[PDB]
Length: 230
Image (cartoon, rainbow, N blue to C red; front, side):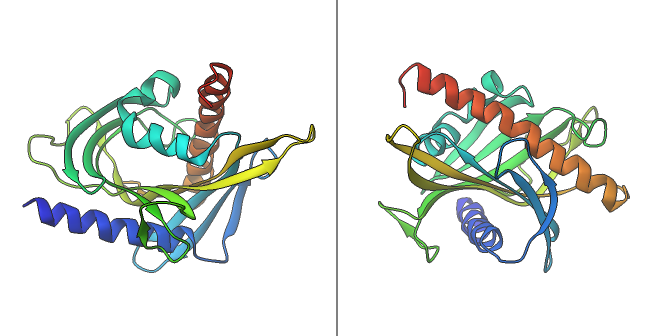
């Protein structure tokens, strides 16, 4: 039934918004760009969740549209994304997707495929879905079993317990006096790694996988600004 999936995605978006806005994180790794940090925390009945925080020089809305509507275009500008299909679109910004990723953590996170149920909504500062003027833009994700899209014997089927892109609009003033649209880019990740790989190893790998990803996001943004798309 469709509604079993609609409920799973709304529940997943709320879990993600609530988690990503929780206080008191543990800094795992810092990034090259001032402000970039991958933090972590223990979350009841999830485990050790991870969060990248960083500032992106583009309207939050624009990044939101790219994730929502151009998911299949991700492999073109992000080499860590091998494949991106939209399996089904099921209403209220909800959809199923099949994603294939490449290796990370210099050999720890092997190439994995994913069956993702997403929720796409504009959230208020209270976490209610609004139609305009939002505190942030959410693109949630959670792994689901979809018949016809089973695990391949030749690839690890990864499991996203909870995740999201949480993008907050930020109009800043530049050194040259100009007023411009920017975005607070937050990324939640709770990927269960099958087997018993000791936690200190995973902390380095997940943090690396995240900091590596943001290099391409900024390349996508810089190019989009040059083609005056933003």
